[PDB]
């Protein structure tokens, strides 16, 4: 059931036709950007994981 | 890069003694602090997925 | 014709009186800041050339 399992993939990702698998192990993920903001009794601190 | 409660590896009830002196610094952004004080607030945003 | 050739220079640049040329070669340019934003079928990525 193609239309069922095709819906599970995320909206941003649309994969191409071919895939040359040449191993018994494949990592899959995404490269996201995190913008953290910290606050406590001592004070405030702002950072960013690129 | 996340923490699940099942990493404790003990079903049931317990109390934890956290070592605050031996807090190593593996990956440091500008946000990263070692000494928390009072009520800790962390607000993060995730954008730019690929 | 001073007023004609003076108009050709960019609005931000106003040069000073003297210039001590001490060679047969001079580079001239500007230091700009570029804020790129990329989007394709795989996902989005945001950068900045400082």
Image (tube, coloured by chain):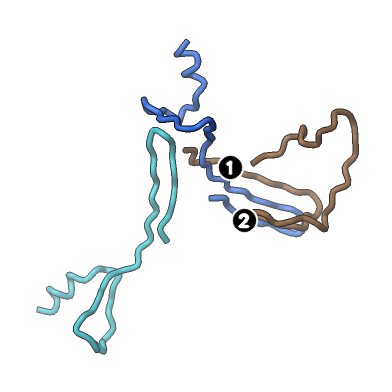
Chain colours: A blue, B brown, C cyan
Q: Residue at x 84, y 52 (%)?
A: B19
**Image position, residue B20 (x, y; %):** 82, 54
Q: From this viewpoint, which residue is outermost toward the top? A: A1
Residue B5: mark in rendering: none
Which of the chains bears the disc numbered 2? B
Q: Nearer the viewer, residue C9 or A8?
A: A8
Q: Which residue is mark 1?
A: B45
Say which of marks 1 and 2 sits in front.
2
Per the image, label 2 sits on a secondary structure element best described as loop
Q: Earlier in the sequence, mark 1 or mark 2?
A: 2
Q: Which mark is residue B29?
A: 2
Residue A14's spot in the image, x, y percent? Answer: 41, 28
Residue C18 appearing in the image: no
Please give the name of the residue rendered at 64% of the width and 56% of the height, measured from the top-left corner: B28
Is residue A35 among what the camera can see?
yes
Q: Nearer the viewer, residue A2 or A27?
A: A27
- Same chain, marks 1 and 2? yes
Horizontal placement of B28 versus C27: left or right?
A: right
Query: Which chain is indicated by disc 1?
Result: B
Cα–Cα span, label 1 and label 2:
15 Å
Q: Where residue A50 sits: x, y (%)? A: 53, 50
Pointer 1 with pointer 2, Cβ within 8 A: no
Q: Which residue occupies the extreme left position in the image?
A: C1
Which of the 4 quarters of the picture holds residue B34?
bottom right
Mark 2 nearby-residue class (10 Å; few <14, some 14–19, many ≥20): few
The spot of residue B2 in percent (x, y) is 67, 39
Tell me the quarter of the picture where residue C9 sits. bottom left
Q: How many marks?
A: 2
Q: Residue at x 64, y 41 (%)?
A: B1
């Amino acid at each position: 059931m193609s239309s069922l399992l095709n819906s599970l993939l995320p909206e941003y990702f649309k994969p191409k036709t071919n895939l040359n698998i040449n191993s018994s192990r494949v990592q899959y993920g995404f490269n996201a950007r995190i913008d953290m903001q910290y606050e406590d009794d001592s004070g405030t601190r702002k950072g960013s994981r690129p | 890069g996340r923490f699940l409660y099942t990493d404790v590896k003990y079903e049931g009830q317990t109390a934890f003694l956290v070592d605050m002196d031996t807090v190593k610094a593996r990956d440091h952004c500008w946000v990263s602090i070692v000494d928390p004080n009072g009520t800790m607030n962390l607000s993060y945003k995730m954008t730019n997925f690929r």
